[PDB]
Image (tube, coloured by chain):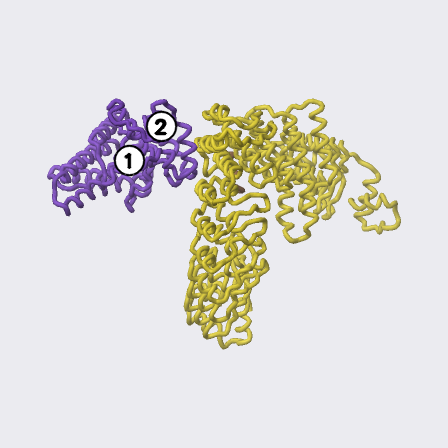
Chain colours: A yellow, B brown, C purple
């Protein structure tokens, strides 16, 4: 039973002996075997008393579980409930990850489940490597470990061992002729993972055992990966390989100098200038066979600086912080290319720093460039548009002015991203559709914020018609959230999530200007929620009528004269007057309610339960339907 | 501050 | 830490007034400063300058002791005197790591000036400059290993400010520049390889001097970054080129050149 399962789980949590013996004996020995072979949802997480004894580290409970009872070690569970949130574990995984050598020792001894394949086909050797303790890995290798497995992330145990801060496991793996040249999911050979967090000893060990230098899926050598992450030590080690070439040496030095310019943990502008100058002097040293820089055409986002192909201009921009920052951005874009994953984040950081210094024009420029790069790479920018809505709120709450082409570009990108978010939601049925739907709703909210700023600025005729074109393009896609709210239900809803950051001030919902903009940009005013409420059943439920009359009045005016049918019944068969938790909303609606005999006759047909099917016009069947 | 919210994705 | 510093300073004063060996006391006291630095706490200047004066006095006394003593005591005095030199280096690193007022910095510079003009030398002949730019300079396994790292671009600039003999030589003839060029972490530490080379060069280091095996600083460079960076700062002079051609062609320069030029051909 579930109650006795919880009882024995609690007994195993404290690691007791007599309580576990009494609670797992005599009474229904078949059910006792079932309980020791059962997994339950405790604390919202799937776990087993045996696997939690392997987790808690209490010895005697697991000794008497594996000795006084014949319990299998193949019981299901969760490999990690923080950062991984995936099930399918075994006792070996939780024993190794927690860090108990003796527990996993007598767990493998009482049943060798070393080749355990979960839902993500990851063996407990991953837990052994992630724990970092050498003894568990030593024993699991002594149990004839098959070191060839790739996870759902397609990473060998060597890759995760090198990515973590543990080098003893890496040394033990390479000491028995492991695979330091084998490829991971994209391109990683554990060098791209050792040269990501700054583990110089792991890189040294892999280089000593000939891990080789090969580009990854993004064309990034481990030297270039280390240079990208501001790892000066790893770049120093990898620049001495007996085959590095001048072009790669100077591009790694330039990338390191550029990376030092725009970063948070490692932000040094003196190191930026010095590494850029060191790579410049290395270019211009011989005169004969002089190495010349492949200067890209100027980019409007980084001011108008066309790189620095001479030491004179580089020395000129030595003392200029902004020039050095944009030079680092240009060098990163040139070396990495405008398609890398890591080429966009420094641009966003420089934009954020500029925004924090009340500098907004080049902030918008840099963030728009990063947004364009991430859209061309087809990546989730539901946070970048939120950052745009927050900075646009900052440019409005501080009484500044916002350029209309900026809002137009952000709105076009938001419309696009909502379109591919709909594509992602509809393409993936149920595999991870929850996060995709949440991103979709967040992106709709960011669009509504952007429309809210668009209503609170001044625009020319061409800019205003472009903005209205983007709003029309979105509103004709019928964007519905998970509860059914169209893009206008949210604009009239009090319970619309506004971000707690700077959008909480400028962007207030319900909005009388956003609603009118959506209405005259072609929004279906008679749109229906999944609950059944129309766009009017929501505004007349507004709980701040007298305080916010101007918003409440102008929305109800806008909807009714924009075509709202002020008699619709939701799936609970309630008119907007019936679903009006406010006397003022009732007064306003009754002022705007235009009576018709079709509405009264449909109300009498619905209320009297008259069978109208196949006795009325087909177009009128819907009319009786929403009455 | 804007630069603080970037640490969520890093 | 104030009470601990005061008690240690009083004990050091009491031991010094009694004419007793204080290399271990100075070493432990510098370890205490390094531990306090590692905790990011405000550092007083007067105790720094007082212990600098005590350290230079102790180094002078150590030289006096090693000048005439038995052979086992010669080894003991040499070890203690080199340890005193290293502790003075750690104290200079601590002094330049913290913030001090104008008069306190002037007193610290005066103490460093006094020790520099005392001209201390280790077994191999390393002066204070040849140790502040040497990556093989030993650092104690205690808290001094956390903040006292050598080569240091701030100790060297302090020694150059106080007037260390830049072109001084070891027993092998290596200048203070023959030592920083062969640094093993050029790219990783392109701030103490640059701010030292650009400091020694502008302080008057001959970037052509030959050691006992006739190897110039850019010939004694074990990495390509130092060669690139040294050749940027080096300046040409016809006295250097002509002396180099005299040495290369094995011409007799004995009594056919000025006495002050027989030394110039000696190392160029």
Camera-side residue of C235 and A484? C235
Label 2 SS: helix
Quarter of the image where one finds residue C230: top left
Q: Which quadrant would the N terminus of chain C be assigned to in this image?
A: top left
**Whether marks 1 and 2 lie on the same chain:** yes
Camera-side residue of A331 and C74? C74
Q: Which mark is residue A407?
A: none
Above or below C254: residue C186: below
Mark 1 crowdedness (10 Å alpha carbons): few <14, some 14-19, many ≥20? many
Camera-side residue of A29 and C174? C174
Q: Answer whether labels 1 and 2 touch (C-beta < 8 Å).
A: no
Q: Where in the figure is residue A166, as x and y percent of width and height?
A: 44, 53
Q: Where in the figure is residue C72, as x and y percent of width and height?
A: 15, 47
Residue A203 appearing in the image: yes
Mark 2 crowdedness (10 Å alpha carbons): few <14, some 14-19, many ≥20? some
Quarter of the image where one finds residue A367: top right
Q: Which tag, 1 or 2, sits closer to the chain's start?
A: 1
Q: Which mark is residue C173?
A: 1
Q: Which mark is residue C245?
A: 2
Q: Where in the figure is residue A110, as x and y percent of width and height?
A: 48, 71
The reply, left or right, for residue A76 in relation to residue A515 is left
Label 1 resides on the chain identified as: C
Q: Where in the figure is residue A471, as x and y percent of width and height?
A: 70, 33
Q: Residue at x 42, y 58 (%)?
A: A133
Residue furthest to the left in view is C18
Camera-side residue of C247 and B5? C247
Label 1 SS: loop
Q: Which quadrant would the C terminus of chain C be assigned to in this image?
A: top left
Label 2 resides on the chain identified as: C
Spatial separation of the CA atoms under disc 1 and disc 2: 20 Å
């Amino acid at each position: 039973m579930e109650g006795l399962a919880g009882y024995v789980y609690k007994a195993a949590s404290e690691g007791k002996v007599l309580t576990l013996a009494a609670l797992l004996l005599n009474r229904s020995e078949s059910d006792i075997r079932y309980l020791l072979g059962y997994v339950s949802q405790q604390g919202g997480q799937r776990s087993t008393p045996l696997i939690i004894a392997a987790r808690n580290g209490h010895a005697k409970v697991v000794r008497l579980l594996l000795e006084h009872y014949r319990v299998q070690t193949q019981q299901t569970g969760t490999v990690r409930f923080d950062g991984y949130v995936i099930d399918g574990a075994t006792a070996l995984w939780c024993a190794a990850g927690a860090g108990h050598f003796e527990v996993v020792k007598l767990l493998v001894s009482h049943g060798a489940n070393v080749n355990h394949t979960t839902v993500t086909n990851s063996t407990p050797l991953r837990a052994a490597c992630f724990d970092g303790r050498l003894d568990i890995v030593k024993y699991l290798v002594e149990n004839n470990a098959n070191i060839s497995i790739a996870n759902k992330y397609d990473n060998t145990c060597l890759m995760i061992a090198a990515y973590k801060g543990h080098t003893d496991v890496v040394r033990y793996l390479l000491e028995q002729r492991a695979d330091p040249n084998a490829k991971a999911h994209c391109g990683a050979t554990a060098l791209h993972f050792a040269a990501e967090a700054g583990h110089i000893d792991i890189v040294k060990e892999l280089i000593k055992w000939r891990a080789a230098i090969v580009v990854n899926g993004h064309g990034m050598t481990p030297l270039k990966v280390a240079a990208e992450s501001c790892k000066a030590d790893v770049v120093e080690l990898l620049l001495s390989h007996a085959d590095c070439d001048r072009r790669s040496r100077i591009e790694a030095l330039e990338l390191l100098g550029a990376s030092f310019a725009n970063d948070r943990e490692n932000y040094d502008i003196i190191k930026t200038y010095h590494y850029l100058y060191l790579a410049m002097l290395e270019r211009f040293q011989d005169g004969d066979n002089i190495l010349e820089k492949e200067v890209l055409p100027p980019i409007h986002a980084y001011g108008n600086r066309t790189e620095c192909r001479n030491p004179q201009e580089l020395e000129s921009i030595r003392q200029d912080r902004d020039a050095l920052h944009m030079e680092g951005l240009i060098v990163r874009e040139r070396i990495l290319g405008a398609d890398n994953i890591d080429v966009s984040h420094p641009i966003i950081y420089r934009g954020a720093v500029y925004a924090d210094n009340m500098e907004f024009e080049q902030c918008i420029k840099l963030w728009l460039h990063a947004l364009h790069l991430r859209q061309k790479g087809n990546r989730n920018t539901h946070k970048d548009l939120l950052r745009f809505a927050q900075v646009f709120s900052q440019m409005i709450h501080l009484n500044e002015t916002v350029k209309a082409p900026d809002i137009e570009c952000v709105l076009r990108c938001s419309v696009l991203e909502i379109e591919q978010s709909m594509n992602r939601v509809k393409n993936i049925s149920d595999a991870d559709v929850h996060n995709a739907m949440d991103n979709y709703e967040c992106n709709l909210y960011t669009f509504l914020y952007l429309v809210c700023i668009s209503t609170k600025t001044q625009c020319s005729e061409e800019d205003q018609c472009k903005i209205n074109k983007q709003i029309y393009n979105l509103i004709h896609l019928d964007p519905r959230t998970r509860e059914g709210f169209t893009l206008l239900h949210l604009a009239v809803n009090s319970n619309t999530p506004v971000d707690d950051f700077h959008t909480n001030d400028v962007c207030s919902f319900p909005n009388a200007l956003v609603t009118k903009l959506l209405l005259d940009c072609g929004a279906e005013v008679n749109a229906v929620d999944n609950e059944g409420n129309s766009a009017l059943h929501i505004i007349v439920q507004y709980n701040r009528p007298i305080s916010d009359f101007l918003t409440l009045h102008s929305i109800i005016i806008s909807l009714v004269e924009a075509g709202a049918h002020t008699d619709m019944t939701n799936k609970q068969n309630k008119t907007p007057l019936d679903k009006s938790t406010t006397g003022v909303s009732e007064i306003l609606l009754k002022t705007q309610m235009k009576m018709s005999l079709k509405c009264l006759a449909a109300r009498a047909v619905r209320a009297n339960d008259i069978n109208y099917q196949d006795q009325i016009p087909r177009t009128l069947e819907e009319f009786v339907g929403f009455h | 501050k804007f630069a603080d919210h970037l640490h969520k994705f890093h």
